[PDB]
Image (cartoon, rainbow, N blue to C red):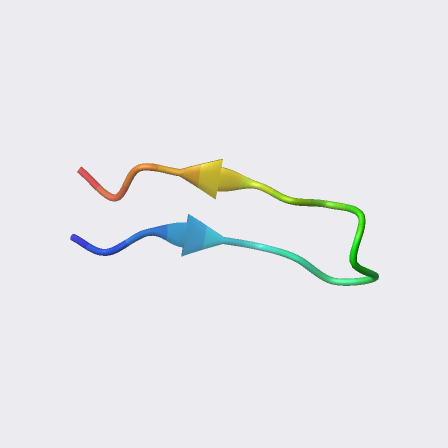
Length: 19
């Protein structure tokens, strides 16, 4: 229960709750 960030080139800012 922390987070799920999948950023690469620096444009894809995927911030999903780790619930």
